[PDB]
Image (cartoon, rainbow, N blue to C red):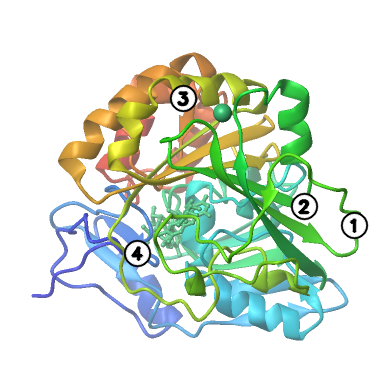
Amino acid sequence: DITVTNWAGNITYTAKELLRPHSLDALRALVADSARVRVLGSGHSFNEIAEPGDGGVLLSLAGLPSVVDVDTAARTVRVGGGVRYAELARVVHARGLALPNMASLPHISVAGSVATGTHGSGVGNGSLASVVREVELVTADGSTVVIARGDERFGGAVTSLGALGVVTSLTLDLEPAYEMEQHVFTELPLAGLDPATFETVMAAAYSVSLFTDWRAPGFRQVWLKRRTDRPLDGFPYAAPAAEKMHPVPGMPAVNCTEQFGVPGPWHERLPHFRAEFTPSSGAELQSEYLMPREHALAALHAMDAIRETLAPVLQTCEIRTVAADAQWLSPAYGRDTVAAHFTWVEDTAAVLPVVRRLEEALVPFAARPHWGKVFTVPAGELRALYPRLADFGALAGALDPAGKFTNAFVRGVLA
Ligand SMILES: *Cc1cc2c(cc1C)nc1c(=O)[nH]c(=O)nc-1n2C[C@H](O)[C@H](O)[C@H](O)COP(=O)(O)OP(=O)(O)OC[C@H]1O[C@@H](n2cnc3c(N)ncnc32)[C@H](O)[C@@H]1O
Ligand SMILES: OC[C@@H](O)[C@@H](O)[C@H](O)[C@@H](O)CO
Ligand SMILES: [Cl-]
């Protein structure tokens, strides 16, 4: 017996072994011979999404080769589902190519990241799932099904909560390698941050994040990640940082990607954390809520008005933008989006009442929770938030009629 947990350690899985097949032949046979299956990627979810239930099989792709195969003429890369972004990015950069975005920390599986709606920031930048052009699935009976952009099912095939089968490979679209500079600023007030000024701030560079502790009024930090092949206007709205910064006040800035406007390659500037920073776990919980971009300032004012409730259990809050997603279950489905992320203290009993209060404040803004993070939004409210959820339920019924890949988390959503 071994104990398998998620990365933060707040979720302990029921599985007494983590199965790690060493060939596709073994993987197909294992899937075909198991009654219920969920896949474990890198465990950077915070809820029971990967839990297969008692007697369910928890399987990993860590025992298969981590393939990264770039076609330079086509500007595409075929990558194993268990490959993490840090390796993917190093490889494609060495071939002269690049991705349009990355999440805050690169040591996360590509298949697991796209499964839940993972994104970075920037008003013109889609989710990480949006560059995927093809997925290859091992389905419930062990057979392989390939689904590509243009297929009428493709909208449900990438961000699928792992509910269609085991993604063994994915193919992503790439662009030429590009250089970036990161400029940090401190103390951006919320007072006077009107709709025009908010839009200007969030569009001031290729990717922009705001950070706050919800203590003193306003925002503690603003991070501008600029492409050197694009203009950068003066940024008058907050003071330039005097020191290297960490998004969480009091944590080690050495861990973070280079600042002070020093040019470097895309994959060493899009993440907030440098590749050398390799935590095996973290003492944190996370939540994030994704809303129509037009509700940004109203939502920020709702949070400000309850900030004394948020602050005591908060490490940092990060505000980002995401372009509309074509994936039916993406929290960014169908609409340009503002995202409000919370990295909490790891105290489940103190955090849940605060999450409930936060969700109540955000209800009129059609807030969709990040599938990989902590939320308490009831299932019926969830279904009402996704116009194409029925299309998804139909696709899952077609590819997995016995619900082999549906666990209690997925079942609750679809019910
Ligand atoms: C821990 C963490 C999380 C995180 C982050 C930084 C850290 C330190 N930064 C993020 C960010 O900047 N933006 C964002 O949107 N999310 C961010 N996160 C969250 C994280 O990216 C997601 O929670 C992600 O889904 C985690 O992926 P991971 O692979 O680590 O997680 P998992 O629990 O094991 O799996 C999640 C789901 O995906 C399914 N899965 C995984 N592999 C497969 C394959 N090969 N086939 C089918 N399904 C797969 C799992 O079953 C589960 O449903
Ligand atoms: O979506 C996760 C979020 O991006 C998180 O990684 C913060 O950036 C981090 O906790 C700040 O330290
Ligand atoms: Cl203010």
Given the image, on which type of amino acid does mark 1 rest?
Answer: Arg
For ligand 1, which image quadrant applies?
Answer: bottom left
Given the image, on which type of amino acid does mark 3 rest?
Answer: Asp
Question: Residue 230, which numbered label?
Answer: 1
The answer to whether the residue bearing label 3 lies less than 8 angstroms from the nearest atom of ligand 3 is no
At mark 3, the secondary structure is helix
Task: Indicate whether 268 appears above or below 344.
Answer: below
Name which of mark 2 and mark 3 comes first in the sequence. 2
Q: How far apart are marks 1 and 4 (CA)?
A: 39 Å
Given the image, on which type of amino acid does mark 2 rest?
Answer: Tyr
- Residue holding disc 2: 206
The structure residue drawn at horizontal position 78% and vertical position 84%, both measured from the top left corner, is 95
Contact, CB < 8 Å: mark 3 with mark 1? no
Task: Indicate whether 257 appears above or below 23.
Answer: above
Question: Residue 76, which numbered label?
Answer: none
At mark 2, the secondary structure is loop
Question: Residue 40, which numbered label?
Answer: 4
Contact, CB < 8 Å: mark 1 with mark 4? no
